[PDB]
Image 1 (cartoon, each protein chain N blue to C red):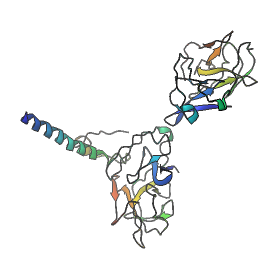
Image 2 (image 1 turned 90 degrees about the horizontal axis):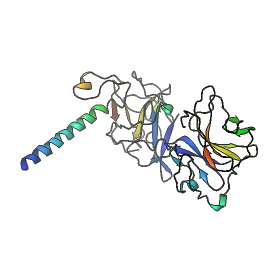
Image 3 (image 1 turned 135 degrees about the vertical axis):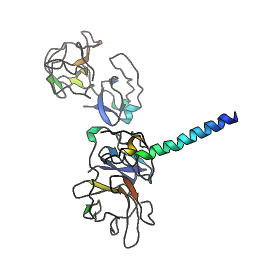
Image 4 (image 1 turned 180 degrees about the vertical axis):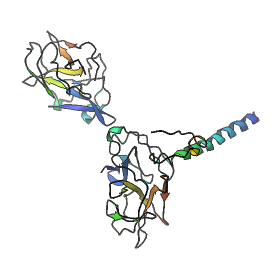
Length: 52
Length: 151
Length: 151
């Protein structure tokens, strides 16, 4: 019961910092939809594909 | 142009602007927009990059267009006057620099918005403005000079 | 006259008419009446006749007078033209008959309301109205053509 608490806390903390990294991927680029997008930051580091 | 202000108990303390595809609102003010179509939108908070949500449909969208690349240090228009500066913001005289002027857009000669002010009350003989802009390749950055109070 | 609109998300999608004693608002539309004296009225559901409670205060009772039977085919006015038929309404031409219009009174030459428009967007060469009507001895009916999409 102590071992499943470590595997639950560290799971929801690592994906919490990953969700912050996912969120900060976009707000440089959702603010200017006319700007072009590199192919490295589209699918490798972040999730958003090319749209519009 | 279209730039609706922000109300709080009658007095004017903030301004909200509409760009192509989105709406903006500064975080240094609290209040409700008097427009009913602009009040039911889920405005989500963000960092200093100032991400908001333009959930309004197309039929009133794109009152003005955001500025492209190739920014000179030439003439730029302003609600109280004019500014001629690209790296920093111009040393405008007094009068402008009061309270509640946050969110007023800075436009070019061709009616295209360049920067949105957020601070810089009074910095002596030369007054600077803390604005957001796109630095070199369209990435939206925030510029703040030294000692910039929230204005 | 008096016909206050109903606004959902700022835009206008329908109109609520006030007949003598009772305010009639269609329920196929949704929203809130902008009047503070009418938004406090309770909403009572019905069939597609679309009743609402006549809690109108005594200061401003009897806004409009309804019209009973003995109705000639005649010529009857309309907000975007005229309708000249008794059993149904006139097949009005295209253009008139858009969206966000259902709820208009149809009045006589004396100003007596005889119908309330609900449906009938497109009916071939000319669009045919789907209104509520009072029958040969003063009972409210609903008259629809075949395949009439509502507003």
